[PDB]
Amino acid sequence: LPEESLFFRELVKQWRAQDSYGTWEKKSDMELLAPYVLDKEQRRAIPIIGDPDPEILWRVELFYNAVGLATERASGVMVSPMMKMSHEGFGRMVLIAGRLIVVNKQLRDVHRFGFPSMEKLAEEGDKLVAGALEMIEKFPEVARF
Amino acid sequence: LPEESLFFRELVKQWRAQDSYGTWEKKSDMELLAPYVLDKEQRRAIPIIGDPDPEILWRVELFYNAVGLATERASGVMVSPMMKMSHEGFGRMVLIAGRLIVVNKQLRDVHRFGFPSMEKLAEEGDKLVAGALEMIEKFPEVARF
């Protein structure tokens, strides 16, 4: 159930935290996160010209923030992102626990960031948390350094 | 001897590599790196207003590039930087070997980046390489991941 994903709950919480004035308080959690969703073909048609819109960069940042906070909830180890955009839709995102890189991602075509359904959004976030947990388990002294 | 520091030699090499047209080919290596040097009091007087000049950011970037390449020369493990500047003279610089953060630095007052003498520049770069080597030695499977 999407609403029972640790990642999903952390993503809802990330967006509620940005809403300082409670402007979206009447929106359901699913409406709040609906911008992460768009069907395959529409998303693949989006060009890669210049820098992605800042709105897209916020979505990506908060998405990885949510992976980090879900990983901490499942492990007790703090996990924080560091993103560095390169030339255009290219960049790098790492998630760091202590001195351990628990998620490493070379980002491309960032303008097209999105998922075909809310269920798929949750599933992909969950996969990232699973990978991060696997790394912390293999190298716990580095994760807690 | 400054010229026998692995870090120092890598820093010379970094700057020679930027000089596509060989404009500084007649400058000695020490003249080439002299911008990294300025006496204590002049450097401490520099204000922290807005973003540091891009020239300063290049000096910092190539400095950490040199730490990474010296570390690889002494270990056989590739080590690459990732910097992310924050609000003003604040930022973060990590050096990554595999999935291991071998150098972690919270940068502040970056506008004031510099050293009191060429010898001191080499000595401080050498300390960073030493620390990076110590990390790779403790966690070699993470360093080569």
Image (cartoon, coloured by chain):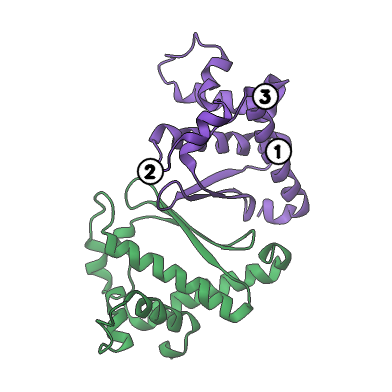
Chain colours: A purple, B green
Amino acid of disc 1: Lys
The numbered disc on residue A127 is: 1
Residue at 47% over, 85% down: B5
CA gap, disc 3 to disc 2? Answer: 29 Å
Q: Position of residue A21 (x, y in %)?
A: 40, 16
Callout 3 and callout 2 share a chain = yes
Q: Quadrant of residue A120?
A: top right
- The kind of secondary structure element at disc 3 is helix
The label nearer to you, 2 versus 1, is 2
Q: Position of residue A61 (x, y in %)?
A: 50, 38
Residue for badge 2:
A49
The label nearer to you, 1 versus 3, is 3
| Nearer to us in this view, B117 or B91 | B91
- The kind of secondary structure element at disc 1 is helix
Q: Is residue B3 left or right of residue B130?
A: left
Q: In the picture, which quadrant includes the C terminus of chain B?
A: bottom right
Which of the marked residues, 1 or 3, is nearer the chain's N terminus?
3
CA gap, disc 2 to disc 1? Answer: 29 Å
Q: Chain of mark 2?
A: A
Residue at 45% over, 35% down: A46
Amino acid of disc 2: Ile
Q: Chain of mark 1?
A: A
Task: Reply above or below: B137 against A111.
Answer: below
Q: Are marks 3 and 2 in contact (CB under 8 Å)?
A: no
CA gap, disc 1 to disc 3? Answer: 12 Å
Amino acid of disc 3: Glu
Residue for badge 3:
A119
